[PDB]
Image (spheres, coloured by chain):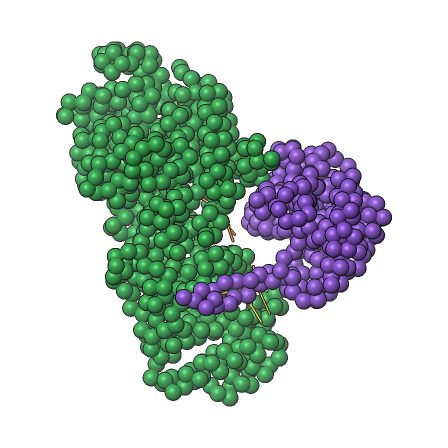
Chain colours: A purple, B green, C yellow, D orange
RNA sequence: AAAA
RNA sequence: AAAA
């Protein structure tokens, strides 16, 4: 399908590449500060109603990266000293570029990125006994940063997502682009978002936050995921986003 | 006895003839000579079972009458039960799969052979060497100690496996050239396949062409997170010890519930186990229950951190051997189910989508009920009661550390020997030394040394194994290097094998070294940075000799502020091990370095390349024991200037300024003055690029 | 190999 | 993290 890519152009280091649950968190929060809980309730309605956001992924210049579907890991058997070696780099790769992501979905041969346009950096400081602690920062290469996908009505985007994201930039600037992802029709899907599943999935990595999510790249069969309202005593009800961002995916019979 | 115990013990003792024919005790071939040895042994001591077991080494009419003379009823067997045992073990011997002076040839290098010795970790390092005759006076000494030990052993597979392991690991199973299979391994896989055929309900070519066997594999995943992410060294060893017990608890559970023997364990090393079992409905139901119950327990105990992936594949006798490599092909279909299962982690818990006594981690542990006084730690099925020298052991099975000798344990107790590399530096207090005390013992800079090591392409090596007994020799020999000999290497043994290695000091009597883990094909070791640096080279050399020079390690080294949390140290050395692998294997990441990012400049060194650099440069600048040469006491500046020059080569390897500078201020480093065209044409770095690996280490030693 |  |  086609989507709106929200490019976060960074004005300094980030602390995390945010996944869908924290992007929804921040967006929901911003909308509360701007239009009140009335508007938070409408944002939730639009998402439950079919709207979706992905987790944030790297971009470099005009290159968009997407999560490597876990579907290809069992399929990698599709030399003797080249299979094992490449096979261990396919298993280690977190991201493919758009073109290679679309090939992986159809179980066709694809290549891995050689560079990732960011670097996780553990910065050390002595804590006066003395100990050493680390704060991780994401330094972006030049004309690089992070983007997420929006799927749904333009009026929900213009009225909630766009204004939320500018408020959130206040550190980053925001620009919007059309992105087309060619995906095969299939009973099975990849999520571009972390998700609270309603069924047991096909293939998955777990993600503990306390909440148990399946990771971006996990494979589901007709799992739309779900949101959780819950009470932490902190005035407003808090909504937790765990809806799936499905793209169709060809599986090998295993 | 019972048919089970009989078929297992018979599988084991089928080939005891081989060492007696080669000791020249009874003139005949191994078959008859084996019968004679056990019959002679039965009449000695007076244990009639040895005459019943004697039948195994030998159109049935004669045997039917020999079986009747023995009166099966005396042992609670039918005549018919014994015929099956004999036919089963005979088939098991084929599926498990010429002078008599021929030694065992090395599974690592079939062109080289082992001298005759008994398995002893306290004695000399097994080194494949030149092919020698073993005298029928070495075999005669063996067969006597073998006869003395069998006279005393209770005659259960758990009291027999060890004495067969002491004495027959370094014996060729068949005296042909290029033969790789240890007799002990051939024996344990024959017992393994025998008991499985019995349990699969087959009797009197049926089980051979049918899928009557299961290959069971268990792989733990998240071991790094379970071990290295916490909140101290004590804790790290305790988690490592804990994982090994959890793994044994699951392995012995499967053996117990399927009615199998320790001989059915092909391997249990590095968080991987493989078991041969019967393919019955009862067995698959029993595995699913165990798999489900072990996963639920892991989830409750450690959350999503430590998963256990357990899979089994239906397999036929055909597939235990070649037909043009069906065994490797079967092992490949099993691996694939394990990868799928590792992408369905905790999928056996439908509920999924809705330490005070640890640190203390004596002669072993008793495997008892979870509810029992004295239980120090609990696994998914059983409690573990520490077994102390001055105390009595508790439990059905007893795990005994670093011996093949049952010791003063009760006769009803199943003997389970386990080997673990647990070397550690003893402190004035007598406790295991801390990160701080190890760092403090360093030459020059006080930093903690950390090394992570890995055999290169182990998976490849194991998949050129045709047979269970071959794989069994491969896995055991590989495991024993790490579990058995790394302690000895740390103590300073095998000096003549090891030779001159990169070194900053005289090797201490009691090294400032603590093992976190050494087993399977891997090690994680910490200590004084200069001792860890040297130990990388000692271990790589010992390992090269242990193999035939046909297998290689890669190592990641790092030198850290003693206050650096484990998780960082483990990530940095993990990254450097991965780097050494990706740059071509048989490499060491010696120290953190800068380089041109021109795709031509490797961060790690080929082991021999670093060793030649050290030989060439270290003696010209370094006296030893924290001391620069006298020449260099007032010119220590030359060393920093070379590193400053090397930085301008890193800035641009193509800009030829660095070469003008090298000529002007240098006859201590002549091979760095001229530009080396040979390197330029070969698309490789200038010698200056490599020199930091030696200089940075000397400058650390001499601060 | 943002422990370049 | 090549069987930790």
Residue closer to the observer: B267 or B56? B267
Left or right? Give the position of B638 relative to B480: right
Residue B151, quarter of picture? top left
Number of numbered markers: 0
Left or right? Give the position of B296 relative to A188: left
Residue B491, quarter of picture? bottom left
Up/down of A32 relative to B344, above or below: below
* Residue B284 visible (yes or no): yes
* Residue A87 visible (yes or no): no
Q: Residue at x 48, y 56 (%)?
A: B567
Residue closer to the observer: B178 or B230? B230
- The x, y position of residue A12, in whole percent, is 67, 67
- The x, y position of residue B264, in whole percent, is 38, 31
Up/down of B681 relative to A138, above or below: below
Left or right? Give the position of B266 relative to A99: left
Q: Residue at x 34, y 81 (%)?
A: B629
Residue closer to the observer: B422 or A47? A47
- The x, y position of residue B253, in whole percent, is 39, 30
Residue B18, quarter of picture? top left
Q: Residue furthest right?
A: A155
Q: Residue at x 60, y 60 (%)?
A: A120
Q: Residue at x 56, y 81 (%)?
A: B658
Up/down of B191 relative to B593, above or below: above
Left or right? Give the position of B269 relative to B575: left
- The x, y position of residue B72, in whole percent, is 26, 13
Quarter of the C terminus of chain B within the rendering = bottom left
Quarter of the N terminus of chain B within the rendering = top left
């Amino acid at each position: 399908p086609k989507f709106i890519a929200v490019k976060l152009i960074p004005k300094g280091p980030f602390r995390d590449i945010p996944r869908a649950d924290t992007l929804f968190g921040a967006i929901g929060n911003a909308i509360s500060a701007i239009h009140g809980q009335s508007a938070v309730e409408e944002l939730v309605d639009a998402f439950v109603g079919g709207a979706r956001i992905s987790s944030a992924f790297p971009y470099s210049g005009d290159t968009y990266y997407l999560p490597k579907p876990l579907s290809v890991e069992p399929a990698l058997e599709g030399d003797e000293e080249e299979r094992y070696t490449t096979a261990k780099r396919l298993r280690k790769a977190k991201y493919l570029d758009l073109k290679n992501f679309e090939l992986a979905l159809r179980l066709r041969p694809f290549t891995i990125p050689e560079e990732i346009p960011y670097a996780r950096v553990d910065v050390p400081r002595v804590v006066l006994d003395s100990s050493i602690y680390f704060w991780e920062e994401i330094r972006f290469r030049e004309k690089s940063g992070v983007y997420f996908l929006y799927s749904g009505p333009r009026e929900v985007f213009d009225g909630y997502i766009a204004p939320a994201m500018r408020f959130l930039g206040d550190l980053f600037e925001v620009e919007f682009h059309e992105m087309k992802i060619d995906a095969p029709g299939s009973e099975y899907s990849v999520t571009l978002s972390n998700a609270l599943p309603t069924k047991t999935p096909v293939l998955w990595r777990l993600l503990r936050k306390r909440m148990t999510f399946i990771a971006e790249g996990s494979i589901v069969k007709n799992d739309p995921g779900g949101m959780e309202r819950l009470e932490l005593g902190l005035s407003h009800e808090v909504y937790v986003y765990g809806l799936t961002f499905p793209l169709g995916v060809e599986l090998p019979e295993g | 006895m019972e048919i089970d115990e009989l078929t297992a013990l018979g599988g084991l003792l089928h080939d005891i003839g081989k060492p007696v024919q080669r000791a020249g005790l009874y003139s005949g071939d191994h078959s008859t000579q084996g019968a004679r040895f056990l019959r002679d042994l039965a009449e000695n001591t007076g244990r009639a079972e040895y005459e019943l077991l004697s039948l195994f080494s030998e159109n049935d009419e004669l045997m039917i009458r020999r079986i009747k003379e023995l009166s099966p009823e005396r042992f609670g067997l039918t005549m018919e039960d014994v015929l099956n045992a004999l036919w089963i073990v005979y088939e098991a011997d084929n599926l498990a799969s010429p002078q008599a002076s021929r030694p065992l040839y090395s599974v690592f290098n079939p062109g080289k052979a082992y001298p005759w010795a008994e398995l002893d970790f306290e004695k000399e390092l097994p080194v494949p060497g030149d092919v020698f005759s073993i005298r029928s006076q070495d075999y005669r000494e063996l067969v006597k100690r073998l006869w003395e030990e069998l006279s005393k052993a209770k005659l259960r597979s758990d009291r027999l496996l060890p004495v067969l392991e002491k004495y027959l690991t370094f014996v060729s199973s068949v005296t042909s050239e290029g033969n790789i299979i240890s007799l002990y391994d051939h024996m344990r896989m024959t017992s393994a396949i025998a008991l499985a055929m019995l349990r699969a309900g087959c009797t009197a070519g049926r089980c051979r062409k049918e899928k009557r066997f299961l290959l069971i594999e268990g792989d733990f995943s998240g071991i790094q997170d379970f071990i290295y992410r916490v909140s101290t060294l004590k804790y790290l060893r305790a988690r490592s010890a804990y994982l090994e017990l959890i793994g044994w608890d699951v392995v012995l559970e499967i053996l117990s519930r399927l009615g199998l023997t320790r001989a059915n364990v092909v391997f249990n090393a590095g968080g991987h186990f493989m078991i041969i079992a019967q393919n019955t409905p009862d067995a698959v139901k029993e595995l699913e229950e165990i798999r489900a119950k072990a996963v639920e327990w892991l989830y409750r105990e450690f959350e999503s951190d430590l998963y256990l992936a357990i899979e089994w594949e239906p397999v036929s006798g055909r597939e235990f051997g070649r037909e043009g490599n069906l065994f490797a092909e079967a092992r490949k279909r099993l691996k694939h189910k394990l990868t799928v299962r590792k992408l369905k982690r905790f999928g056996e818990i439908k509920g999924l989508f809705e330490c005070n006594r640890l640190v203390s981690l004596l002669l072993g542990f008793g495997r008892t009920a979870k509810n029992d006084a004295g239980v120090l730690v609990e696994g998914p099925f059983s409690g573990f009661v520490p077994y102390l020298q001055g105390g009595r052991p508790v439990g059905e099975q007893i795990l005994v550390k670093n011996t093949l000798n049952p010791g003063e344990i009760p006769e009803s107790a199943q003997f389970v020997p386990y080997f673990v590399a647990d070397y550690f530096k003893k402190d004035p207090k007598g406790g295991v030394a801390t990160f701080e005390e190890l760092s403090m013992a360093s030459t020059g800079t006080r930093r903690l040394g950390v090394m992570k090591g890995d055999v290169d392409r182990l998976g490849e090596f194991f998949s050129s194994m045709d047979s269970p007994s071959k794989l069994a020799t491969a896995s055991r020999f590989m495991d024993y290097f790490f579990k058995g000999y790394i302690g000895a290497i740390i103590e300073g043994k095998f000096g003549y094998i090891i030779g001159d290695v990169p070194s900053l000091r005289d090797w201490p009597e009691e090294p400032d070294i603590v093992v976190v883990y050494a087993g399977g094909d891997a090690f994680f070791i910490v200590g004084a940075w200069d001792q860890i640096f040297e130990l990388a080279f000692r271990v790589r050399r010992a390992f090269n000799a242990y193999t035939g020079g046909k297998l290689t390690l890669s190592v990641g080294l790092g030198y850290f502020d003693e206050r650096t949390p484990i998780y960082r140290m483990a990530d940095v050395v993990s990254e450097r091990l991965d780097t050494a692998k990706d740059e071509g294997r048989n490499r060491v990441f010696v120290v953190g370095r800068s380089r041109p990012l021109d795709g031509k400049h490797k961060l790690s060194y080929e082991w021999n390349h670093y060793e030649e650099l050290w030989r060439t440069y270290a003696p010209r600048i370094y006296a030893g024991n924290g001391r620069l040469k006298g020449k260099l006491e007032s010119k220590k500046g030359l060393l920093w200037k070379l590193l400053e020059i090397r930085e301008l080569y890193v800035r641009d390897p193509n800009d030829v300024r660095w070469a003008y500078l090298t000529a002007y201020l240098l006859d201590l480093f002549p091979e760095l003055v001229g530009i080396d065209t040979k390197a330029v044409e070969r698309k490789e770095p200038q010698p200056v690029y490599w020199v930091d690996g030696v200089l940075k280490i000397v400058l650390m030693a001499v601060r």
